[PDB]
Amino acid sequence: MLQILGKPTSINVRKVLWTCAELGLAFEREDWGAGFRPTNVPEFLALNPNAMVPVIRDGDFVLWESNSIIRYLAGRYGGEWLYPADARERARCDQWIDWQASELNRSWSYAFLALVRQSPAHRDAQQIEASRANWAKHMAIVEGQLQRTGAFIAGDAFSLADIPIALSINRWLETPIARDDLPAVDAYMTRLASRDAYREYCRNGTP
Ligand SMILES: N[C@@H](CCC(=O)N[C@@H](CS)C(=O)NCC(=O)O)C(=O)O
């Protein structure tokens, strides 16, 4: 059985859990990460030198990096409906997957660590606000794209890209910041409510 190493509250672990549920995979999950089981130990470092979650073990195959993992699962487990093989259709998904990780995630760092994790190391109000402002600019880009599609992030159909993106939106909505009205974003999160795995792993009260 596929093994998922990572605490269930982690946004990046939740990408993998949601993907597994969408595809129809059986899995066992072990708690790893801050607050759960420390990752900076030899047994875990041997699997992932970053000492971060998620990591998966699929038979003898070990893989880390959440967006790489969800791509792997969709490619391995009959996920062509979720992550299409056509290069242009796949690219429309990849743009948002990759931007989620390289830009959107990056933008929320200080505000999230300060306000949600209450990190004693992140108490500079100016940096909290800078992070909130930058995050807000990235959310306006998400709003623009959803205004255009009127549906899902990459087009008319739910796709792999909606998993990192909707989890990121959830983080925005659950962090205690003042937020501009983004109606296409709200309508999108309402649309997703019909998906059981979204309710289980995304909009579940955990930031
Ligand atoms: N880029 C990595 C980031 C992984 C990451 O930052 N994981 C967090 C949890 S969301 C973590 O393991 N922090 C270290 C810890 O909890 O000890 C990915 O997307 O998988």
Image: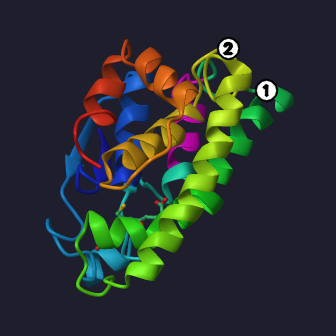
Q: Is the residue 172 above or below the residue 126 in the image?
A: above
Q: Position of residue 194 (x, y in %)?
A: 37, 12
List the residue tagged with mark 1. 89
Q: Amino acid at mark 1?
A: Glu
Magenta highlight on residue 65: no
Write down the quadrant of residue 126 in the picture.
bottom left
The circle drawn on residue 156 is: 2
Which amino acid, by three-letter code, is at mark 2? Asp
Earlier-in-chain disc, 2 versus 1: 1
| Residue 12 percent across, percent down from the top left | 41, 53
Whether residue 59 is visible: no
Q: Report the coloring of the rendering.
A: rainbow
Q: Residue at x 75, y 27 (%)?
A: 85
Confirm or deny contact between disc 2 and disc 1 (CB under 8 A). Answer: no
Mark 1 secondary-structure assignment: helix
* Residue 116 against residue 153 in the figure, above or below: below
Q: Nearer the viewer, residue 203 or 123?
A: 123
Side of 86 where 136 appears, left or right: left
Occupied quadrant, residue 40: bottom left
Magenta-tinted stretch: 69-79
Residue at 41%, 19% in the rendered image: 190
**Image vertical order of residue 189 relative to residue 167, above or below:** above
Distance (Cα) linking label 2 and label 1? 11 Å
Please state the total of marks drawn on the protein image. 2
Q: Position of residue 50 (x, y in %)?
A: 44, 77
Give ligand 1's quarter of the image. Answer: bottom left
Q: Is residue 132 visible?
A: yes
Q: Quadrant of the N terminus?
A: top left
Residue 32 placement, left or right of 138: left
Q: Position of residue 9 (x, y in %)?
A: 24, 51
Judging depth in this view, the residue of 113 and 33 nearest the camera is 113
Q: Nearer the viewer, residue 206 or 131?
A: 131
